[PDB]
Amino acid sequence: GSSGSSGKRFEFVGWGSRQLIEFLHSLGKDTSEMISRYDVSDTIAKYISKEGLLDPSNKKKVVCDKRLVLLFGTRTIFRMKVYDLLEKHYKENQDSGPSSG
Image 1: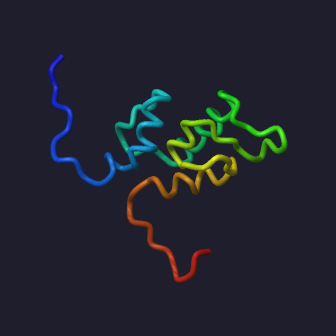
Image 2: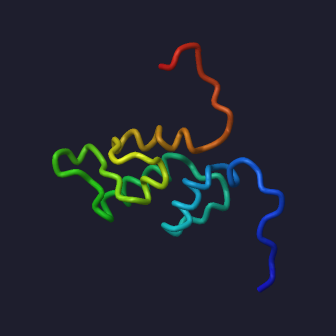
């Protein structure tokens, strides 16, 4: 083997934030080409269950364990919010307004 690593670090790490990246890296996701949110989100929904982050009081919710925390930084979230949660991480200018609906 013999390859570079990284030169001249800049905002984010590719298309998504390191947080999301790393998280995907660990899981074993090949953050090669811009992945579709739905996917990452879908994987999250699976991972949440896979690991068992789900909540007993309400499965509809999600109880972050660590990875999710290091990702979002929250203790609990909505299995759905996931999509949005990522919507943030992911780069790419997102035009919207006026108002935050």
